[PDB]
């Protein structure tokens, strides 16, 4: 049978350990996939530290992958109806939803499925066939996985990264009920989520894209990938930033704001930048935090504002994200600062934790 | 023509009776005899000097129905009917500039920064003076959006509906799906929330639940269509959440209307809202202390929409009259007092004390 | 157990009564005792071999309500409730693949090319055989979308609603605004149009006008909420257009539903539609000769939306059940005949001749 | 003492436009006197010249596509962003003024459908002072109700003038689509200015694939140059070949979104067969009553669950968004301007547009 290896999380806050798995057969309808690129996410650090309550042990982490089909045990179609075969290059939606609940079937919001099963997050490696995350030479995909064939003209590293931060960013923009033509977009934060938001905002036809953050290196990147204006929170005052946005928008404020900071306190700045009638997509905050002092009359009622929380993404967002991403490979590849062998998965988590890396991608040896 | 009005000359001092002689009216204007004038809870705040838009002196009253006396030129209503002396009409209290970003580009006229409103930011010092409904007569500018009504319409109900009803309608109109199969929770049982009951019912909501503190208002909400009322003073937060969870199979409410006037209503409402739900916030009407808002739990993880609602526009006005017109007998139950115009000071006192739910004034 | 069903062996051959011995059912499947089975006009086309989807032999019947006999394993309804013996249920006739572009990307499961439908494209020759509602029992796959109902629900009405009702609902669901203040014109007064009357009313339409040729169906349309009916034998096309222009102040209808089954309906409907109006075309159910379409006048100059409507999905299912549940007394009037299952041929005959509006079959 | 202006006046249908001079002193309260710098010649100007548009009074100064420079404002005028206009400002404006009082303007919020819509160079004659109500002129007088946008010396006024008509109608067509264009396949029928602006708008909104079907190789080459992924020449392929091409690109589904930009009702016969189940078809090119086409209701509407949406002109929201898209694509869109003529050659301009020797002509005073 097949000799696979992976980096396994056995106990929280303890280094991932190398382990080998002999793969004999795979479940009916499943797809055995050779991982070619595996994204390391900020959230993987959180999971490693034992702060994500969905996470069983032991587990093969890694929810962002691109790979080559080794074997389908039976037949599997991709989302366009193409039958997969050995050697096909694919990406896939990390989440499988039930297809039977209120959100999957009635409201058509499958990202809200309470039964959502996610590779490298709530799928452990204890029970055979074990290989349920991307920090591995190989992953076994269930037959219910949403898959998309890609080609050798696709940058698999970029696609892997895009699966997570990109598709969330896409969801955030997709909730806006108008075209972006003529619109001013403000993005708070310049990690992968905010930076995909720059390229997504550009690609959907936004007039002006402004990014507010605190790292000059990340802000330079934002400019190289399409931002019209960047504002460094450490070099400018709140009022200076408000005036720059008010100047650009003829005194109205921004039409659409993306929170991509991870910090609930971002809404305090963002609310004062939003025009009357504007739309604030809140997608960065990823853990419970202290409550923020929210001014209901000023920020919601008087402003006639929409505040929209964004929870992950579904298959519609996945395919649309691949499509935008595929027009933007050269720019988006600039987000990958580090490329490491799988056996260095621990160092990769350190790099991400310390912010030495913007994004790290692992490759099996 | 000799008109009279009850005029606000000094905040916190009683409205005073005053006579006005109306000869010429401005070009294009419509002189209207007031038949019904609603006394709104916001008029109390204006009376008390709490509204910074309010010039003095001013004839208050932004909620009106009346009879056309004359048109200086020609005026069509929204359906294109030329107005003539004798016609009965209602009208939108607000006039927008029709030239700014919100009027012409984003098509959100309610957000017009140049919005002019009878009985609110239009004083009575300058001729022709009559720019509010606490008067025998009002002069409507040509730009006013008007609708003709008939003798089969209830003008008292229509006056009331103009304000609270049209804001309630705006709150429901922002919901991007139909209300079929949906559970609606309304927080509050003043005019705003009670209109919400009738609008929710009228748009097809499956369940309409009202949370408030007054048994008399809760009985009324039942009478006009609520499936369930929950008295906030006689139940726990946890009991009310359980009741809503039982009705929605453990999910929560699809749509919540905040109609209390208290920002703290979001603390409870946020925990009733299903994942993916929609919270329209329309009641809070003054700057208040900030509330501790749980961004992850209430917005992000919930994938929720919080939508603030500012007043209403002409599309909301027309839709509100249409709903109201199919519900006159239910909605007339909100009017607890009808007083002559000269007793306007008592009307304000009734509304302030909540001895009244809604007061209508009539001239003479 | 020994079930019985009425089987279609050859097109145009009378349905044959047959017994089926059921020993065990596939894993996760649900064995359901049929309590009400609706006979649809589309069953007549199937019976004659006009529907190219139809395998033979087949147990027809795609409108069903029933009582759970057994689940081989466990099955949750759409609200997550575990089904158990004795539960009353309704279900979506169609099961979609959950994997294709329509199911997963555009979220239009009604357009699934792999859609499997009880009594339509599921034959009865392979065990467990019972894949249609003209039967004492049906075996539902684990993938079926089910909803529990109660003894307070009218199951005869629910069976009917599953088809025509959910298609009507889809047609209204596509309209991008509220129905408040709107005038709705419905063409045709069979079950689709009649459900259209009730739905239009329930979503808050101001005026509902029905145009058809059957006096008795038009009387029923008034009994269930139409404001005006217009009979094509008794009125001219010009008289109809004037009546609709009078109600809409010269503009035309805001929303039209085609529910006649005839392509030529568009000729009249296009001239009743306001500029900017919305025309949902849901009745035409077979390929027909092309109609002469005036692209400039009816689409471009009118800035009109013509929207075709193909069946329905689980979202429309639940929402239809929800509106129907509030209108059982009105909608019961559509059921003109109830016949034992063994009389299924006569039921198809009644539906073909239009002596019935809707027939319900009951086992035993 | 007054301002000396001149224009090319249509006095009688099918007779040459005639040069005439005017002296402009007073203008109506609130009005803006504008020096024309660019005037687009539209294909519909030909039909109006010929006496085919029932809206057209005589005499009239044609030209509904314009950009220019503020000479004077009688009072005050703010552009749509709130900026006060002053003499010397460069502007563009919406050709159409709506009443702001009717059902469509106030209730349904569809001002393009206002029955009282007043359009420079179309239904506004030139015989009553101050006369200058069209762009085939040295100057135009804009009413206070006109929606205006200030532009800069870095904007291409020739491209903006053209964009005002064909471009805003194409924008309207795309704006009616209820989803994002991400991952979508767009087919455009026709490669005149309307269809060609469609290409740039489709690209700008993020469409994945943009395909153009037309009959002219030159125009199909232009469509490729401004961002089309594929062109199909309908004179050199069968309907079946074109459908196969679209089916191959869309994994056998059909187009997500089609724009009819041909002017021929018969285009729907092919487009309907290219549309996927659940697809959206904006019909914007057909501009005059035509014979009815044989429409297959079951196959093209019902079974397809298709949306067919007719597109009538545009409003100020479309205007502003068109100017924004256009402003990022000046160099591509300038490729559409094939001829620039002096105002006094307006008759030759119409000839060029009618013969189709020109794709788009711009007129310039002086
Ligand atoms: Zn689910
Ligand atoms: Zn991730
Ligand atoms: Zn009020
Ligand atoms: Zn304004
Ligand atoms: Zn049926
Ligand atoms: Zn499918
Ligand atoms: Zn033009
Ligand atoms: Zn108008």
Image (cartoon, coloured by chain):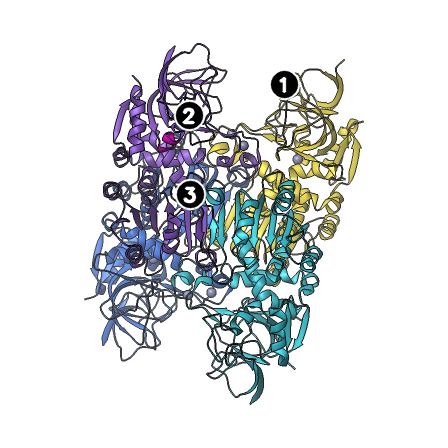
Chain colours: A cyan, B purple, C blue, D yellow
Indicate the quadrant where residue B13 lies.
top left
**Does residue A196 appear left or right of residue A296 in this picture?**
right
Q: Is residue A266 above or below residue B288?
A: below
In this view, the mark in front (1 or 2): 2
Residue B205 in sight here? yes
Residue D47: give x, y in percent of width and height. 66, 32
Residue B351: give x, y in percent of width and height. 31, 32
- Which residue is tagged 2? B119
**Does residue A79 appear left or right of residue D68 in this picture?**
left
- Crowding at dot 3, Cα within 10 Å, few <14 / some 14-19 / many 20+, comes out as some
Residue B234 colored in magenta in the image = no
- Crowding at dot 2, Cα within 10 Å, few <14 / some 14-19 / many 20+, comes out as many
Whether label 1 lies within 8 Å of ligand 8 gets the answer no
Residue D93: give x, y in percent of width and height. 65, 32
Q: Which residues are magenta?
A: B41-45
Which residue occupies 38% across, 53% down? C167
Badge 1: chain ID: D
The C terminus of chain B, quarter of image: top left
Number of numbered discs present?
3
- Which residue is tagged 3? B173
Residue at disc 2, secondary structure: loop
Residue A83: give x, y in percent of width and height. 55, 73
Residue at disc 3, secondary structure: helix
Query: How far is the residue under mark 1 from the one under mark 2?
Result: 32 Å
Outermost residue, left side: C364
- Per the rendering, the mark at residue D28 is 1
């Amino acid at each position: 049978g097949l000799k696979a290896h992976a980096m396994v999380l056995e106990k929280f806050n303890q280094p991932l350990v190398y382990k080998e798995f002999e793969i004999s057969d795979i479940p009916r309808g499943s797809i055995l996939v050779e991982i070619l690129s595996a994204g390391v996410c900020g959230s993987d650090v959180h999971m490693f530290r034992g702060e994500d309550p969905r996470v069983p042990l032991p587990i093969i982490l890694g929810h962002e992958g691109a790979g080559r089909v080794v074997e389908v045990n039976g037949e599997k179609r991709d989302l366009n109806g193409e039958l997969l075969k050995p050697g096909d290059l694919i990406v896939w939606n990390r989440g499988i939803t039930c297809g039977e609940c209120y959100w999957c079937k009635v409201s058509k919001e499958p990202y809200l499925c309470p039964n959502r099963k996610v590779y490298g997050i709530n799928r452990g490696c204890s029970e055979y066939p074990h290989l349920r995350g991307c920090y591995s030479s190989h992953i076994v995909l269930d037959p219910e996985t949403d898959v998309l064939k890609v080609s050798e003209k696709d940058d698999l590293d970029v696609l892997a990264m895009a699966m997570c931060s990109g598709a969330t960013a896409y969801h955030a923009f997709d909730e806006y009920p108008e075209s972006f033509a003529g619109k001013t977009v403000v993005i708070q934060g310049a990690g992968p989520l905010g930076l995909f938001g720059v390229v997504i905002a550009r690609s959907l036809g936004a007039e002006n894209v402004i990014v507010i953050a605190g790292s000059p290196n990340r802000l330079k990147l934002a400019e190289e990938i399409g931002a019209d204006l960047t504002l460094n929170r450490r070099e400018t005052s709140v009022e200076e930033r408000r005036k720059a946005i008010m100047d650009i928008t003829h005194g109205r404020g921004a039409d659409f704001i993306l929170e991509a900071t991870g910090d609930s306190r971002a809404l305090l700045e963002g609310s004062e930048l939003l025009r009357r009638g504007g739309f604030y997509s809140v997608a960065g905050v990823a853990v419970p935090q202290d409550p923020v002092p929210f001014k209901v009359y000023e920020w919601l009622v008087l402003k006639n504002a929409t505040f929209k929380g964004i929870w992950v993404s579904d298959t519609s967002h996945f395919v649309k994200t691949v499509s935008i991403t595929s027009r933007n490979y050269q720019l988006l590849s600039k987000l990958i600062t580090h490329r490491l062998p799988l056996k260095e998965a621990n160092k990769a988590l350190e790099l991400m934790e310390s912010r030495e890396a913007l994004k790290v991608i692992l490759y099996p040896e």
